[PDB]
Image (cartoon, rainbow, N blue to C red; front, side, top):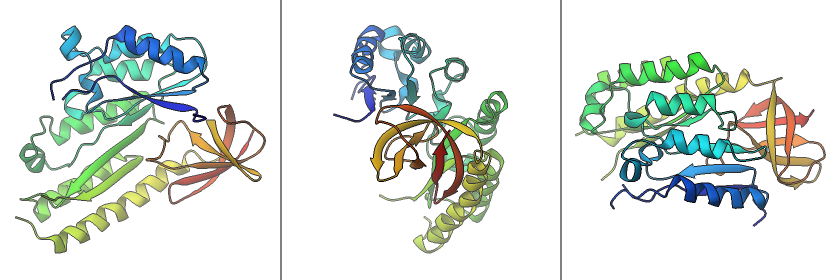
Length: 272
C-alpha cells in the first residue's frame, strides 16, 4: 500500500507465547524499509514479553538494537508495553537507540494499590511512578501513554482520590479512561470517568504546550489541498492525534515542522 508505516508482529502468544526470531523479524523489517516504509511499529499482546519463550529472557532490548542498526532514516515505535514487565534493560534500550521514538505505551489501569492488586497487577503505584519519573528524568520530552479503568468493583472515593493524584503526579501526555464491564454503581462511575478525562485534558494540553514553537520530525502521510497531513513522532497511527502542516512534500517523506497551535489533541504547524 502507500502507507509509510507498518505493524510488525513480534509474537502472537500470551494461547501459548510464541516469539519470532530476532533474525526473522529483522529480515521482515529490512524488506519493509526497502519498499519505502519509514515507521516500524512493533506489536504483540505484550511486547515486553518478547523472547521469553525463545531466548529464555526478555530479548526486546536485543531486538531493538538489531532493528536500530538497519540502514536508513526511519522510526521504530513500540506499543502495548506491560508495566509489570517494563524492565530497566528495555527502558534504557528505548532511550538509548536513536531510531526508537521515546514513546511509551504502558497502560497502568489504575493508581490505587488496592485496585491494582485486585486487578492482578504486581508493581505498586509508587513503583509505577518511580519508573515513569525515571524515564522523564532522562528524557523530559518522553511521551507517556496509558489507559485507566474507572468503576472497578470495590473502587471507593478513596481509591479514585489516589488515582487522581496519581495521574496528577505522573503527567501522562496521553491517557484513556474506560468504565469497567462484564460492587460500584455506574452513576458515580460516569462522574469519575468525566472527571478523570476533565483533569487529564488539562494535563494533555499542558504537555502539548511545551511542543509549541519547537522543531519536530514530521512524517507525511497525505495531502489535502494546501495542507500536509501526517504525524510527529509523538503520535501513533489511528489511535492518537494528527498533525496538519502547510507546505510542500510527498507522502513517506520526513520533514522538519514547527507546531504553532493544538486543539482536541490535534496539531497545526508549518514546514521549516
